[PDB]
Image (tube, coloured by chain):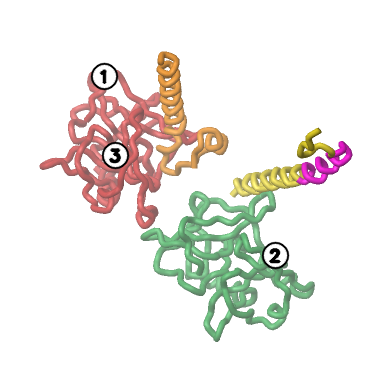
Chain colours: A green, B red, C orange, D yellow
Amino acid sequence: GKRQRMVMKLESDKTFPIMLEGKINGYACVVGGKLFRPMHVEGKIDNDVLAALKTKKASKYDLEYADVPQNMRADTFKYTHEKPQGYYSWHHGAVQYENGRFTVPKGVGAKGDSGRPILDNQGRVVAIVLGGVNEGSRTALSVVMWNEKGVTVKYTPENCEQW
Amino acid sequence: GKRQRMVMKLESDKTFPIMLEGKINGYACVVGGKLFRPMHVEGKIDNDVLAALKTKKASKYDLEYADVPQNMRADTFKYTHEKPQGYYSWHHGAVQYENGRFTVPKGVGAKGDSGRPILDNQGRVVAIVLGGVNEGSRTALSVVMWNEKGVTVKYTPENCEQW
Amino acid sequence: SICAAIATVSVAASTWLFCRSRVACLTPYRLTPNARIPFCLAVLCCAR
Amino acid sequence: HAQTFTAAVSKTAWTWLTSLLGGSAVIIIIGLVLATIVAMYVLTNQKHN
């Protein structure tokens, strides 16, 4: 429960829910100085400054990137590409990273918890959750991430449902 | 002793015996999301989910092999290319690995001993037993295995018996 | 008739040896639990 | 004499029909080759994980 306190205290400032008729459908993430928002999530950004923007579309990677004003570029997530195997710290507890795939134990994951970042033990974002499929006792995840070259990579398992 | 009990705990979940008319002829392994079955063993897999799946055949490596359904993919074994010399585990006690040869002290290994996955000191499958020959006071085995490149390698000593 | 017979036997035997060689190349990569076919052999032997 | 079809086509006009119709095929095949190389390079970039 100690890692989930860290995730909630880092999401209290830098994560914004995308509300449609009050209902949560997704989360905009401000990482590295650029706003991120998925395509299929419908609604508006909770923050008033971020809602009045012109988000350039990128339909392949299921993202709608934007740019952050200069007074807000220090209040962003830090991020990295470095990802050894083991455990990472999601919003609902922990998430296993094995063979280049983020897996969460089952039950959790429904319509609405998309766009949530995955943190490491230092406090840096390594992935952004878009969707996932339930492989029985454990749910694989479809995320975007980065690499050592500096290239945004999206991983997508089979038959993933958009969250 | 102690080593065999965690192997029984693993084999109770994922290693499935075949059903000849009154007895057990062989054992289907579910590793990495790909069901494995030896050829000379004939019968029916105990699960009605694993029975209906049509298998592709590889006569050089003596194994039928089909793809496992999506729910079962998380509840599979794991496989390892790297094996150092020493001692590995097996359902009938221990198995020695020396000069690339899985050998077993004699008195054990007979008919109905096929498809049993040789585990390691962590719980990952390094080989699959298909039979062996009595090399004097200690029997060697005829297993398939994997290497660093991703190439299924079968080793077989002289005049082995299809168990 | 003998030209047609030699042509049919040659095309059938060459197609049989080609299928044997394609199976003998693609078999050690389809048996692995991940089935990660390398890209050049997937371009050549028409794999997934 | 007999008027063959394409009898008076005047090699200048053969050049104008070869350039403005065959050259557009050259444009579309180098566009298709460029698109194929771009798709393979994007897949090579995403081989990194």
Q: Main secondary structure of the magenta part?
A: helix
- Determine the secondary structure under disc 3: strand
User: Where does label 2 land, which residue?
Assistant: A32
Residue A138 in percent (x, y) is at 40, 60
- Magenta extent: D9-24
Total labels: the figure holds 3
Looking at the picture, does residue D13 appear above or below residue A36? above
Side of C34 relative to D8 (left or right):
left
Q: Are marks 2 and 3 in contact (CB under 8 Å)?
A: no
The residue positioned farthest toward the left in the image shown: B22
Tag 2: residue type?
Answer: Gly
Looking at the picture, does residue C12 appear above or below residue C33? above
User: Disc 1 or disc 2, which is closer to the eye?
Assistant: 1
User: Where does label 1 land, which residue?
Assistant: B159
Q: Residue at the location (52% across, 60% down)?
A: A142
Tag 1: residue type?
Answer: Asn
Quarter placement of the N terminus of chain B: top left
Residue A65 in percent (x, y) is at 68, 67
User: Disc 2 or disc 3, which is closer to the eye?
Assistant: 3
